Amino acid sequence: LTIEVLVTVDGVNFRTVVLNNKNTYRSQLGCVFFNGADISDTIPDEKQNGHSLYLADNLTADETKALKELYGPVDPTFLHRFYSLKAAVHKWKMVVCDKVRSLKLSDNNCYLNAVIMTLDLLKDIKFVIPALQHAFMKHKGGDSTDFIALIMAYGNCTFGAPDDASRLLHTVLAKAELCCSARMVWREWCNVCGIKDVVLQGLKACCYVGVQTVEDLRARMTYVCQCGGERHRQIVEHTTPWLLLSGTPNEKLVTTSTAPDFVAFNVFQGVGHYVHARLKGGLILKFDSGTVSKTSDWKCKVTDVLFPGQKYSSDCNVVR
Ligand SMILES: [Zn+2]
């Protein structure tokens, strides 16, 4: 007729809550998850007495603090969306392929395979957000469920919907940080406004959206200045541990040999499908969502391309 439950937001700190059987959990407490089940619209009964619940809204001040410290500044629906995802993707299998883990195709999740396999190549990145960092470590140790559900929640991904690998990869990488230093110095100039430098540091210096080759990235770019005249930009210095370049699907013929400068790339095939590729030992290792395959030549549409560390200084006075 009345029960006691433990309520948490972090799996560490629980508060005791007393409930009766005269309204639903949602009326008395909030949106609650009991071992992955949304029992919010249930009338509490004996079989939940003593059990631990995850709360997703109507937090105490102390819980709101732990939420922000653990997950970051998230929107109200976050915890709800995360709990749902965590449960929905529990059944996803991480298949071992050529000694590398890959995400088996289920529910249009092919884009997540490209994302996770690409992240696994990125040397020495950590996530600022503790919950995400713990999940990532847990993922590298063989349990990928929390990490998959977390990046899906932060990325506003919907279970079962097809999505874009480049989109999520950059959205996830926006929440990371490097162990070393990284620098990118853009030199900008206009004949009216004058000359200024724009520096990007750390993770913002390793990722770029809009070109897919280093030659195009390092090129003089011309656009319209805020004064309406002609403005120019050019990388004048670039030091990074790796470089991820992303563009729209680009039909290309990848061959070995000659040795490409890039160590991996992602491909789109067109709902659409995503394949992760690595260059290892003079071959292209195609990872098709739990599947491997090897070829020396591939005509594919590349999207993201991953390069090794950059050590670049211009030996040109780019302004003249
Ligand atoms: Zn100008």
Image (cartoon, grey):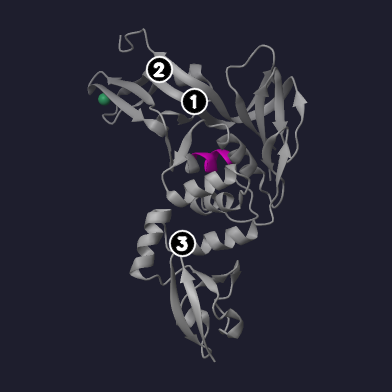
At label 3, the amino acid type is Asp
Q: Which residue is mark 2?
A: 220
Check disc 3 and report the residue beneath it: 10
The CA distance from mark 3 to mark 2 is 49 Å
Question: Considering only vertical position in the picture, is 285 above or below 86?
Answer: above
Which is more foreground, mark 3 or mark 2? 3
Mark 1 element type: strand
- Local packing at callout 2 (Cα closer than 10 Å; few below 14, some 14-19, many 20+) is some
The earlier-in-sequence mark between 2 and 1 is 2
Task: Give the residues drawn in magenta, as a range.
Answer: 165-170
Looking at the image, is mark 3 or mark 1 earlier in the sequence?
A: 3
Q: Amino acid at mark 2?
A: Arg
Task: Check contact, mark 3 vs mark 2: CB within 8 A.
Answer: no
Badge 1 is on which residue?
242
Helix, strand or loop: magenta stretch: helix
Which badge, 3 or 2, is on the more N-terminal residue?
3
Q: CA distance from mark 2 to mark 1?
A: 22 Å
> Dot 3 surroundings within 10 Å: few (below 14), some, or many (20 or more)?
some
Give the image location of residue 132, x and y in percent. Answer: 48, 49
Residue 260: percent from the left, percent from the top?
62, 16
Label 3: element kind = loop
